[PDB]
Amino acid sequence: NGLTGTGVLTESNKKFLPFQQFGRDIADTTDAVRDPQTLEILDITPCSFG
Amino acid sequence: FQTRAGCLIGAEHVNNSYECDIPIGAGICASYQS
Amino acid sequence: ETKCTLKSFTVEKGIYQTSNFRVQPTESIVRFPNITNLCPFGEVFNATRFASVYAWNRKRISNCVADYSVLYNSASFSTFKCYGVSPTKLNDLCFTNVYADSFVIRGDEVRQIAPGQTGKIADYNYKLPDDFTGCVIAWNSNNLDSKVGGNYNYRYRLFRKSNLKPFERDISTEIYQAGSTPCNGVQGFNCYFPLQSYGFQPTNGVGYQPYRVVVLSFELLHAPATVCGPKKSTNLVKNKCVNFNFNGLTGTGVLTESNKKFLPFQQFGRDIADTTDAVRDPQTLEILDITPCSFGGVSVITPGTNTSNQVAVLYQGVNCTEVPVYSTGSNVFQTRAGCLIGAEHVNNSYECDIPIGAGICASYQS
Amino acid sequence: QCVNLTTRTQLPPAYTNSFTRGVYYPDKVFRSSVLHSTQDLFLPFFSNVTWFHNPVLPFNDGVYFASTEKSNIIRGWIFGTTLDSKTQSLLIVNNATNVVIKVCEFQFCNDPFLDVYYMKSEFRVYSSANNCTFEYVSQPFLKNLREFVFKNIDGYFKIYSKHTPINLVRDLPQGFSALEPLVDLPIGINITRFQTLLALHRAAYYVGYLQPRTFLLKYNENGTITDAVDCALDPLS
Amino acid sequence: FNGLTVLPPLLTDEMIAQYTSALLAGTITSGWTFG
Amino acid sequence: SSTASALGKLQDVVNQNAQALNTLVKQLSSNFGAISSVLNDILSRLDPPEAEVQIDRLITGRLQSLQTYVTQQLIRAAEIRASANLAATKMSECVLGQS
Amino acid sequence: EAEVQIDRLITGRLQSLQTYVTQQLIRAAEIRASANLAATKMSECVLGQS
Amino acid sequence: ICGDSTECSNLLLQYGSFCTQLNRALTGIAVEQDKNTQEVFAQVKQIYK
Amino acid sequence: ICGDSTECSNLLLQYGSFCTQLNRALTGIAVEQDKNTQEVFAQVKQIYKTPPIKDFGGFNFSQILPDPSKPSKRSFIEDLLFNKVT
Ligand SMILES: *[C@@H]1O[C@H](CO)[C@@H](O[C@@H]2O[C@H](CO)[C@@H](O)[C@H](O)[C@H]2NC(C)=O)[C@H](O)[C@H]1NC(C)=O
Ligand SMILES: *[C@@H]1O[C@H](CO)[C@@H](O[C@@H]2O[C@H](CO)[C@@H](O)[C@H](O)[C@H]2NC(C)=O)[C@H](O)[C@H]1NC(C)=O
Ligand SMILES: *[C@@H]1O[C@H](CO)[C@@H](O[C@@H]2O[C@H](CO)[C@@H](O)[C@H](O)[C@H]2NC(C)=O)[C@H](O)[C@H]1NC(C)=O
Ligand SMILES: *[C@@H]1O[C@H](CO)[C@@H](O[C@@H]2O[C@H](CO)[C@@H](O)[C@H](O)[C@H]2NC(C)=O)[C@H](O)[C@H]1NC(C)=O
Ligand SMILES: *[C@@H]1O[C@H](CO)[C@@H](O[C@@H]2O[C@H](CO)[C@@H](O)[C@H](O)[C@H]2NC(C)=O)[C@H](O)[C@H]1NC(C)=O
Ligand SMILES: *[C@@H]1O[C@H](CO)[C@@H](O[C@@H]2O[C@H](CO)[C@@H](O)[C@H](O)[C@H]2NC(C)=O)[C@H](O)[C@H]1NC(C)=O
Ligand SMILES: *[C@@H]1O[C@H](CO)[C@@H](O)[C@H](O)[C@H]1NC(C)=O
Ligand SMILES: *[C@@H]1O[C@H](CO)[C@@H](O)[C@H](O)[C@H]1NC(C)=O
Ligand SMILES: *[C@@H]1O[C@H](CO)[C@@H](O)[C@H](O)[C@H]1NC(C)=O
Ligand SMILES: *[C@@H]1O[C@H](CO)[C@@H](O)[C@H](O)[C@H]1NC(C)=O
Ligand SMILES: *[C@@H]1O[C@H](CO)[C@@H](O)[C@H](O)[C@H]1NC(C)=O
Ligand SMILES: *[C@@H]1O[C@H](CO)[C@@H](O)[C@H](O)[C@H]1NC(C)=O
C-alpha cells in the first residue's frame, strides 16, 4: 500500500485497533503491516547480515 | 559448528578444554593441531 | 616578529616559533620533444560537405602541433563554448588523441548539445556524457548549406526503442511499431520511419536555417603526449631549485642525475605515497630525479625584553649551507636540531635555561 | 583464392589448469620495493584454460593466447564480427620479415591458410579487400613458449607479449613471468570473434579468457613484478 | 538494526562467578598466602 | 636474547604512530568530489570562477582530515601521559625503597 | 542534482558517525581508568591487608 | 550511510579511506574491554574450592 | 593544504584562525613528551659512580652495569633491548 521496504514477513499476534494500517516502535522503524486484501497483521524483520 | 557468536566452518569441535589462544567468543576459542 | 605573533609589547624569556622558511625558485626550464609538424585544421573546419546529425562525421587527430590562437580570435563562429578548459590556456597545454565531431543541425537545437541536457537531438542523435570535457563551436551556414530548391538530404532521428548511449552511432533504419501490432514493413497506422527530413530554405527565418557544429574532445594524461601547441623548448639545469614543465607535468624542485634502473617503456617513476620521484626528459631520454627544495620552521631564542633586546635564530632541520636579514650576523653553529645564528659556542656545561634540543641549550650571559 | 578444407582436422578441446599465468604490467609508472594493489582485467588463478592439439572462438573481453610452438609455425591472427567485407576486419601477420597489421573490409573463405612452397612464397588467406582503414608495419615478433594478451579498451587494442624458453613436455610451466606492454593500436573496432593461422607444408596452443578483479603485486629492487596475489580466490588470499 | 551489531563478551557470566568463588575460597582458607 | 615479541607495547606504539602518519599522508590523493586530486592541474587547466569552487572542495576535505588526525593524537597523548605517571610512581616507590 | 542531494546526505551522516565515534573513545578512556582502579583495589584489599 | 545503493556507494568511493580507521577504532575499543575484564578478574593461578 | 599556491592561501584566509589552533596543540604535545621523560628519569641530584673494585658479597652485577668498552656505554641488557625492537 505504498509502504516499501526489504525484509522477511512472518505471522504476528499483534492486535491493531480497527483503523490503523501499520506499526512501529522507536525512531520510525516499521515493524508490522496490515495487508489490504486479507486484512491481517503480519510482522517484518530485516534480512540477515554481518 | 554453531556457536553463540555465529557459525564456524573449517573447524572440529572437541570435548576437551585447553588454554585459550585464539579467542573466538562466548567462552570458546580455537587452536591448531588441523 | 615575536611581538606581532604573541600580540604583546613585552616578551618573557623563552624560545618561540614564529614562521617558516622556504627556498625560492631561481629560473624556469621547459623541455618538449623536437616535433614541429603542422596540424590539419582547415581540412575539417572548411570541409564543403558535412554529414547529417545521425551520421555525424567522426575524426581522430594526433601527432601534430595545433595553434588555438588563430581559431580563438576568429569571428566566423557564432557560438564558442568550452567546459573543462579555459580557452586562453589551450595554447599552453598538451593532449593526446583529439577527437573532432562535425555535423549540421537546426538553429534552435544548439542548446541541446550539453552535459546533463535533455531534448530530441541530445538523446536520439548525439548523447554527450555528463562529465564531458572539451569544447563546442557553432556557426550559421544559411548562406551555403541552404538551397532554394529545398534541402531534404539532412535528416534527424525521431524515434527509438529506448535512449542512446554517450558517444554512440546509430544508423539502423527500421519501421517503428508505435502501436500494439507489428508493422511487417508497412509504414501505415502506428508505423513511422525513425528519420525525419528537413525543409531547409533560404526564405525561412531564424530558428530553421542550417547550422554547422564541430565539437572537440580531449583526454587527461592517459598516454605519452603526442599533440601539443606552439611553445619554446629550453635546456636542462642541474642542482638548482627551479620549476619545470616536463611535457605538461609542472613542478618545482631540484633536478639531480639519478641511477635508477628504468625499463625501456616507463616514462616516469615514483615511490611510496605516490610521490613523483624520477622523470625522463623527452629529447634526451635521461633518468632524472626530483627532490623538494629545502624548507623548515624557524624559532627565536630570547632572554626577555624585560632584560635585553638581542635574540638568536634557529633554523630547524636545515644544514648550514643555504641560510639566506641575518645573512651573516654572528658566528654560526651547527647542531643535530638544525643551524643556529646569533649565539657563541662554549666548552662549558651548566644547567639548562632555554631548551633547544639534542641535549644542548642556550642561556644569556651575550 | 582458397577452397574448403576437405581434410577436416579436429583439434581436441581439452581442458587444463591455468596455474599462475597471465600477469602483465598494468601501467607505465616505475616502482621499487612496494606492494601495490590494482583492479583491472586479469586471468583468474587456477582456472580452466582450453587446449587445442581451425574453429571459431569469441573475443569476449580479453584473451590470453599461449603457444609452446616449435620452429615458429604460428603466423598470425584474424579479428572481427563475421569475417566478411560487410564489417570492419583486422589482420595480424608475422612472416619472416617485418610484421604487418591491417584493418580493412577483408573477405575470407571457410578455412584460410598460408601454405609454404619448397622459394617460400604463398599467401591466399583472404579473397577480397576493397575498403581499407588502417595499415601498420613493425619488427618481427619472433622449447620456447610465447604468450600474448589481447585487450580492447576505449578504442585501443593493447597487445602484451612475452616469450621464454621452455623445457617441460606438455603442461604450462608452474613459474612466474610478467608481460611487458608491446603495442597499442589506436583504432576502435567492435570485435567479437577471432581466428588463428598456421604455416602448413604445401598444433597445440592454449586459450583463456579474462575477468575483472583485484590483484596485489610485489615489485623487486629493480622494478620488475616478481610475485602476485589474487584477492577473490581463498580466505587466506 | 541498520548496519550496527553488538558483540558478546569473551568471558561468560559463569566463568566470572567461578573466578569470584575461587578468590573467596582462597582468601577464606589460606589467608593472604595464596597471593 | 632468544624469545622474540617480548616487547609488544613499545612496538605497538611505534606502529600506531607510523600508521597514523601514513594514512594522513595518503589522504592527499582523494578527489573529495572535485574533478582532480592535484591542485596545479586544476589551477592551470580551468577558469578561476569555478576553479575556486574546486579548490574549496579540496580545502574542506583536507581540513577535515587534519582535524581528525589532531584529535586522535590528543587522545593517544593522554593515555601515554597516564602510563608515564604510573611509571614514575613505580620507579619512585620500588627502586628508591622497599614497597 | 540527485547527486548533489546525495552528497548533502552523505556529508551529514558522515559527520554524525564521526561524532559518535569520538564520544565512544572518550567514554572508553574513562572506563579504562575506572577498571585500572578496580584492579588495583582487588590486588591490594582482597589479597592482603592495606 | 548508503543503505545498499550502487550510486551512493560510487559517490562515497571518492572520499578516500574514511571508514577503515573508524572500524579500527571500534575494534580497539572492543579489545580494550576484553582486556579490562580479563585483567581485573583473572588473578588466580588455580581454581580453589 | 595548499602546497605553495597563493590562491589557495587567499581562499583559506577566510576560514578563520584554524591553523593557529591546530599548531598550538602539537607544541603542547611535544612539551608534554619532554616533561614526561624528564620527570620519569631525573629523580636524583648527583651522578653517582660505582667503585672500580666490585665485591658485593658474592652477587654478580656485571650484566647490568655499563660496559666501558662499548662506545654507547650501555649495559648488555640495554643493548639487547635496543637491537630487539626496530
Ligand atoms: C577557412 O578558409 C578561410 C578563408 O575564407 C580562412 O580564413 C582566412 O585565412 C587566411 C589564411 O592566410 C587569413 O589570411 C585570413 O585573414 C582568414 N580570413 C578571411 C576572412 O579570409 C580560414 O582560416 C580557413 N579555416 C581554417 C580552420 O584555417
Ligand atoms: C651540509 O652540506 C655539505 C655540502 O653538501 C656537506 O658536506 C659534504 O659532506 C659529504 C659527507 O662527508 C661529503 O661527501 C661531501 O664532499 C661534502 N661536501 C662539501 C661541499 O663539503 C655536509 O656534510 C652537510 N652537513 C650535514 C650535517 O649533513
Ligand atoms: C558488435 O558486433 C556484434 C556482432 O558480432 C553485434 O552483435 C549484434 O547485436 C545486434 C543488436 O542486439 C543483434 O541484433 C545481432 O544479432 C548481434 N549479432 C550477433 C552475431 O550476435 C554488436 O551489437 C556489435 N556492437 C556494436 C557496438 O556495434
Ligand atoms: C566500400 O566503400 C564503398 C564506398 O563508400 C561502399 O559503397 C557504398 O556503400 C554504402 C553502404 O550502405 C552505400 O550506402 C553507398 O551507396 C555505396 N556507394 C557506392 C558508390 O557504391 C561499399 O559498400 C564498401 N564496401 C563494403 C563491403 O562495405
Ligand atoms: C638488479 O640489477 C642489478 C644491476 O644489474 C643487479 O646487480 C648485478 O647484476 C649483474 C647482471 O644482472 C650481475 O652480474 C651482478 O652479479 C649483480 N650484482 C649483485 C650485487 O647482485 C641485480 O642482481 C638485479 N636484481 C635482480 C633481483 O635481478
Ligand atoms: C659475572 O658474570 C659474568 C657473565 O655474565 C662473568 O663473565 C664471564 O667470565 C668467564 C670467566 O672469566 C668467561 O669465560 C665468560 O666469557 C664471561 N662472560 C661474559 C658474558 O663476559 C663474570 O666472570 C662473573 N663474575 C664473577 C665475579 O663471577
Ligand atoms: C564428545 O564428542 C563427541 C563427538 O564430537 C560427541 O558425540 C559427544 O556428545 C561428546 N561428549 C561426550 C560426553 O561424549
Ligand atoms: C630531437 O632532435 C634533436 C636534434 O638532433 C635531438 O638532439 C633529440 O635527441 C631529438 N629528440 C627526440 C625525442 O627525437
Ligand atoms: C624584570 O622586571 C622587573 C619588574 O618589572 C624588574 O624588577 C627586574 O629587574 C626585571 N629583570 C631584569 C631587568 O632582568
Ligand atoms: C674550547 O673550544 C675551542 C673551540 O670551540 C677549542 O679550540 C679549545 O681547545 C677548547 N678548550 C679550551 C680550553 O679553550
Ligand atoms: C574444469 O573442467 C573440468 C571438465 O572436465 C571440470 O570437471 C572442472 O570442475 C573444471 N574446473 C573448475 C574449477 O570448475
Ligand atoms: C613478408 O611480409 C613483408 C611485409 O612488409 C613483405 O614485404 C615480404 O615480401 C614478405 N615475405 C614473404 C616471403 O612473403
Image: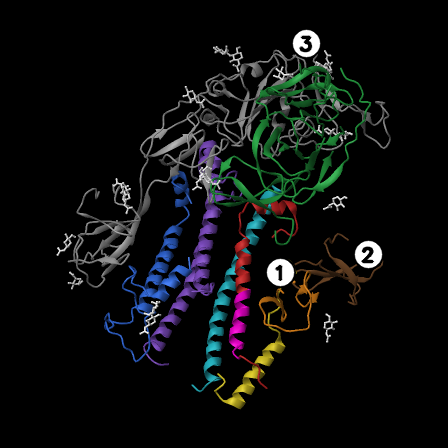
Marks 3,2: beta carbons within 8 A: no
Cβ at disc 1 under 8 Å from ligand 7: no
Q: State whether residue C180 is above or below residue E25.
A: above
| Chain B visual colour | orange
Front label number (2 vs 1)? 1
Quarter of the image for the C terminus of chain C: give it: bottom left
Tell me which chain the residue with mark 3 is part of: C
| Chain H visual colour | red
Query: Which residue is label 3 attached to?
Result: C148
The span shown in magenta is H30-44
| Chain E visual colour | yellow
The chain that appears cyan in the image is G
Q: CA distance from mark 3 to mark 2?
A: 67 Å
Query: Which residue is label 1 attached to?
Result: E4
Q: Residues within 10 Å of mark 3 (few under 14, many from 20)?
A: few
Q: State whether residue I61 is above or below residue H25.
A: below
Residue found at x 51% / y 73%: H39
Marks 1,3: beta carbons within 8 A: no
Q: State whether residue C265 is above or below residue C139.
A: below
The chain that appears purple in the image is F
Tell me which chain the residue with mark 1 is part of: E
Q: Is residue H35 magenta?
A: yes
Tell me which chain the residue with mark 2 is part of: A
The chain that appears blue in the image is I
Q: Say what secondary structure mark 3 lies in.
A: loop
